[PDB]
Amino acid sequence: MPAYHSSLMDPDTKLIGNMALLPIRSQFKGPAPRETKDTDIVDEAIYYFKANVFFKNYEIKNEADRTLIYITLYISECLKKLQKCNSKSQGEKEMYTLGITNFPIPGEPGFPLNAIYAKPANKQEDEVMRAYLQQLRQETGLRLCEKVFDPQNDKPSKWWTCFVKRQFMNKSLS
Amino acid sequence: GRLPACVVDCGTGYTKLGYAGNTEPQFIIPSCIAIKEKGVDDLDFFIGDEAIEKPTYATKWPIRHGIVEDWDLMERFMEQVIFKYLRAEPEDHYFLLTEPPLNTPENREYTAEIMFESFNVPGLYIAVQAVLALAASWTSRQVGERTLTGTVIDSGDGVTHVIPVAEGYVIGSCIKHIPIAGRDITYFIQQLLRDREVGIPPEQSLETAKAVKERYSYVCPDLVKEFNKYDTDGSKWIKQYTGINAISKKEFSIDVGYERFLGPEIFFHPEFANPDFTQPISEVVDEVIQNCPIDVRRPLYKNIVLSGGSTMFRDFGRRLQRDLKRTVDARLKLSEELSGGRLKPKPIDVQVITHHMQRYAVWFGGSMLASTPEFYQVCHTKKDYEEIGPSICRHNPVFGV
Amino acid sequence: TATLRPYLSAVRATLQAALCLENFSSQVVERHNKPEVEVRSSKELLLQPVTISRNEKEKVLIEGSINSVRVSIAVKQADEIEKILCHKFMRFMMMRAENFFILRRKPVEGYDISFLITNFHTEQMYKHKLVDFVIHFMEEIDKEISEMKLSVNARARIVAEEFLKNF
Amino acid sequence: ARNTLSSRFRRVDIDEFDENKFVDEQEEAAAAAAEPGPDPSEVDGLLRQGDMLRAFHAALRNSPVNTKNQAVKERAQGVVLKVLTNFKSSEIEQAVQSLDRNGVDLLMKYIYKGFEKPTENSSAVLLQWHEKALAVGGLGSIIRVLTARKTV
Amino acid sequence: MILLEVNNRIIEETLALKFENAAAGNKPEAVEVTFADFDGVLYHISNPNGDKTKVMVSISLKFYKELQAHGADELLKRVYGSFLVNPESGYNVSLLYDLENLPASKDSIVHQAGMLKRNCFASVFEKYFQFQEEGKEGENRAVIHYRDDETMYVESKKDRVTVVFSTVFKDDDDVVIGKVFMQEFKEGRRASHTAPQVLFSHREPPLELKDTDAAVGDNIGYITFVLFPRHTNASARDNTINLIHTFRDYLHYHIKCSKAYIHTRMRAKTSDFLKVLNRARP
Amino acid sequence: MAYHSFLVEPISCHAWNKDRTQIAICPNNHEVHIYEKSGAKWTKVHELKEHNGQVTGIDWAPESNRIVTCGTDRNAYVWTLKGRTWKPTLVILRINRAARCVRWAPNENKFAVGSGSRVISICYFEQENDWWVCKHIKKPIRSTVLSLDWHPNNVLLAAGSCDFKCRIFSAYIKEVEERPAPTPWGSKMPFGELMFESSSSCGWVHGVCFSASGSRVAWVSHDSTVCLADADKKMAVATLASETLPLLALTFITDNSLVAAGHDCFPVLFTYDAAAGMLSFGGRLDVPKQGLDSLHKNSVSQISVLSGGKAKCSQFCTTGMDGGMSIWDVKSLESALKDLKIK
Amino acid sequence: RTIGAELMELVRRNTGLSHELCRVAIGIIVGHIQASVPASSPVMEQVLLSLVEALPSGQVCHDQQRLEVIFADLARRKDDAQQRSWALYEDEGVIRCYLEELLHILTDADPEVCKKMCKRNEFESVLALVAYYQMEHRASLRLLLLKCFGAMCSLDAAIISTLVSSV
Ligand SMILES: Nc1ncnc2c1ncn2[C@@H]1O[C@H](COP(=O)(O)OP(=O)(O)O)[C@@H](O)[C@H]1O
Ligand SMILES: [Mg+2]
């Protein structure tokens, strides 16, 4: 059967490059509009993370799938740093520092999906992309730390750090 | 007096022996052979349960995907099956063997080349495994109400097959053959635990994965909803398995989590293990039946017989019977729309039954058969071998000419 | 019962004479490319058969053609226990004929083994090494049988001791 | 699967009754009267006195290649094959070196015919003959045995 | 496994399952099992009259009339005793083990249940082994048809017991290898000096049996066993009988298993040649 | 004495352009790869992909620059270089079996294809439909045709077959040329007339080449018997039976001497004396290299004349099953072998 | 222009020397022909400078080829689920041969080759051995892997972060 795709795409949803500039519920600042609903492109990708890393074939139906694939690849970067953390406060400090890092973007080397992603043509669209992703890289990390850490010991769970070796298909943002 | 026939279902995991006429086999042993690590030294070997425990011997598994790979060992595996366990003088007893559908002809030829020349048997019949499993179900069924028409799903350790049967005749050109089975489920649990639960010795990872599979595992209605149930309410769904080390004799314990439903899921998401296969078994069955003649599509949906040890999973038919009825009630809906909506066609009565005998279903259909007189007609014979040669056993129903 | 050096010297020369091959498309079927020595539809493309022999039993038969050669061989079998071990040995050599690319899955009638060498083997494989395999076969086969006859006799003693010792 | 229609038409072979089959040519002049071949009394009278080297050339002078008859060929083979078997092993190089090219090729034809049906010691001799004729005539002598459409 | 086992697995396996269940207090489970052994033997384990507490090990030897003679009816009684009861229908002997009236130390009655075929053959040997010890000569030989196309002649003398097998080799590849195996039994007294003497007449029988309607053929084989009193005495007649009633099957076991040794060795030499050809592959 | 291994597999056929600047090999496949001579290197420039089967014969017309191919798919294609790419042009051979050889004519107005259909197809152009229609010559022939060569009159044709013969035919096409001048081979040369049929009937004729004078033709056989017929001497044949493996292709370097090559994996030379009326072995040409002892490590299937024509050749090319192409320099062999003489 | 690097590859192939002693042997030979034969000093000094101070375009080192062949089989033998948990074929002698060869390369060859082929594709080849170690139970092979890990830690410190963060 197929993997889990994004249901949130709507024709009224803006496009950046060939991705889906979708609303995000965050206190962080960026080009992403603020959402009112109780579900977002982030809460989905965290719902569907543990299941989508076992599949080996993903068919890109729309552009919101290109936004989900990015997060699902970045969550595997959070867990590499979080498994080394001994307290949630130490994780939130590590999740900040990682989002500030300038990962590759569509068009340049490092990005594993340069072919099936559309780079920004103009410089203004480039500046919007680098600030949309950084808004995802920050709210993703902030929301994992609520889940990874067992409140009984305030230390990472083996049920999340078992997916450290499970890349999305085999790709990584590095 | 007149002697019954020997029956042997050499499978990937377990091997089923005995004589005809009986209801359950006289032996059920793993398909292993223990050898040392010229002269009479090729006879220092053990098979079955006498092979696992042997410390100074190397355990070998000569069968993969139902087919044999090293006939140097299987010729030694069969000369203890006969002379040690069964204690049969093969020049007197006929024989019934089993093959999967996709067994090559050259393996059927080397089989008969072994039994007829080396062991000098007077007869031999190489039957299809899952077909015998359907005859067994008919005895559980009422007498006279026997349904000759039925679909069969036989999944063991090596490979999984879907075989339709209509009015007694096998529709061989519509068979499917899914390479996913209990060995792929086991190596997938053996993988998830190496990532999470270190503390399992490498010598006891396999023993630990079968134990989890046979006991704790099950089948889920939806995958991602189970991950939440294991996360949100972990005390209820996470079990614990205490083992015993074999060196220090100290216990080791682990937490049994996502591998309870992820192993069996590869029946429905087989790209978890094998990237060369994506289609679920719920869809393979629909193509098997929709490729069959239009008149025997309904009776085949109504008798889907699960056989094999890797269909013992809890709630396996409940999901297969549900993934089909979704697929079948839609197709009838679409046709009702294209026609004009003037006729509401009759619904199809899907039924997936899971019969009481599974560990020896195929053997049982071979014992009922061998106890007949009709068996002694279709059996290839020593005389027919000397004349025609080992190509007498070259053909199977899966192909023509 | 002549000698072994000249026998292999004759066979080696006849083989170099008969491995003068080239591709050749068929003239009875549209675009087939078969070895004409096997199908034998075109008599003109079939060279003569020539035989070599140390004696009545041992001999070689080179059936050549424009695009194929067939080298049947008869091995000496003094006693019955050698007829058996040679018959099995070829069966286990024919079963792996997809790995011996120059081999027939059955032998010519009257002979114990038969090779078949097409014009695609000489283009790919080294023509002079294929000959050295046929020759190496013909002088080692006698050694590899007596080594089995001696291995059967050694086994029969242990099977006797392991029974009589218990008395 | 299996078929249930008459498939017997695929058994009969029509290629037997074909008009494009190859036809090799024969000598018309020899069908009426065959070449007499080496007469036995000629060679034999030269064998009684031990003149092997001349009984040798007498057998290779006449050869019924153009003859369609097989007995005179067989009689001819038994004559020359009787001669080669009686030679002295040291005298063979003396005899082979005398022959012209076209006699060495005809010799090697008769040699590869002696290997077909051997006596007790007919082949240990012919392998020595084969060594000498090859030293003179080379592989090209054998090729004119393979390509030869007319047997000896 | 070089030597064949004399005690059947299915009986020792089946009874010990019942005997370990009942003595654990669990309830009895039914059973109906038909199976076989060598020499045309046919067993039958059953719950008689449906009584799941009783199990009845029967057996159907042909040639048992030859064994009721020589006093095997008494030999078997001296072993099992109470367990021996009236024969089941179509069968020659029938034991009966009561699951509620079991003794402790069950491994002895189990191990004796597997040896039922042995205890039947063990009469004709103990009778003739005693004749040598008593010095009785002039008694008649014992013709036993342990198979339809085979026969076992026994005979006793002052200093030796002579045991003959009129075996048969179906294929001609077996009679060729068989001469090799028997040609080394004859020389078996070179290593094991105390061992019995063995002989082998290919087609024709010996002189002791030419009058006795023996069979001749290009595939038959006559095999003799000369047993001296260091075998037939009371301390060794058990282990001697445990080997002699398995000889015909020991010989054929190793003819069929020698082929696998040959096959096992040609798959290797074939791979040695295949290294020489791959020299031609660039 | 060069050796450039284009590949490891055979080279069924080859052809050179006028300048000898480009070469068109078939690397044992359905494609024709055109390589250009850039200095001391070889660079591939084009690849012709139209055949449904293996190629067996190629010829390059020097003036028109029109390549013609024949393959096992019962097809031929006439290629014209339009701009930067080669475009084919269809051919109608009308043969039920596969083709084996092709040769352009001297005047480039026709070509002849030899096939396993027991025929030879004389092809010419038809602008009415852009086709190349063909006429057949299949009167005496009884089996496959292996080689061909054109007389300098642009009419007469020689053909070596597996019928053990080297016939000579008149490929006169009235629509494209006037009647020819007479020749010592005969005056009566209508379409499809057997002028000369050889006498030998042992061995398959692999190669055939006409002499520059047009009065001498030689042919090689699998019987290890080179031959040569002279029309001035009433079509008498002179053989020279060799003592080695056969030859597979020949060509006249002069009016008297030839060069052959084949399964012996090197070239040789053959000298003709019409005074005596025989051939003589001119010795091996390539020196034994300082198992095989030459450049070609397998057989040779095609020999061609680059420089000097058949009148007096200075360089000839060999193309073999060892994926190789060796250029030879004739005078360098004269110098490197003081015993060697080219008559 | 590139002699000093094309000679070291020739010498390590036909001698088996380490990287260090490959440069010593050339510096000694050259430095001695320069001194004994002053007529050749200009050529020799260029050759020495090529050593003190890259390879041709398509030319690839021998040690780099082997590490493509070794890391590829050991990862193929890791992904062979049947043979690991359900053994049929013999593997101890082949694996012991590839791990010995690996240990002589990491220990002797140029570290920058053995660094990049281990740092390639985010340490894909290192992390496999780390899993094959977890999967293997035979101490004859667990011991050679340890000697190989101990040689990979000496090359770079990014590999140490990869192993310690692993299982
Ligand atoms: N309760 C169970 N649940 C799931 N699998 C089981 C159960 N019991 C046995 N099995 C599996 O059945 C498999 C063997 O199936 P079977 O068909 O009997 O043998 P084979 O596969 O060799 O033909 C084993 O791999 C075993 O793990
Ligand atoms: Mg099974």
Image (cartoon, rainbow, N blue to C red):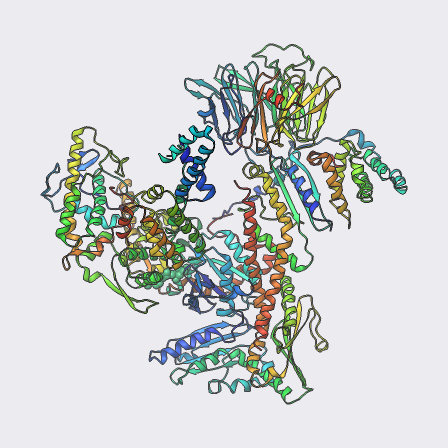
Between E146 and E199, the one lying in front of the other is: E199
What percent of the width, then of the height, locates residue C25?
57, 33
What percent of the width, then of the height, locates residue A165?
27, 50
What percent of the width, then of the height, locates residue E111?
47, 79
Q: Height in image: G7 above or below F15?
A: below
Q: Kindly identify the residue that appears in the image at 58 percent across and 48 percent down.
A: C105
- Position of G4 compared to F258: left or right? left
Q: Residue B233 lies in what quarter of the image?
A: bottom left
Image quadrant of ligand 2? bottom left
Between B57 and F166, the one lying in front of the other is: B57
Q: How many marks?
A: 0
Q: Height in image: B273 above or below D145?
A: below
Toward the bottom, the furthest residue is E134
Q: Residue C49 lies in what quarter of the image?
A: top right
Q: Height in image: G25 above or below B110?
A: above
Q: Quadrant of the N terminus of chain B?
A: bottom right
Residue A13: tell me if it is visible: no
Q: Kindly identify the residue that appears in the image at 75 percent across and 19 percent down.
A: F276
Q: Height in image: E228 above or below B57?
A: below
What percent of the width, then of the height, locates residue F302?
58, 26
Residue A26: tell me if it is visible: yes
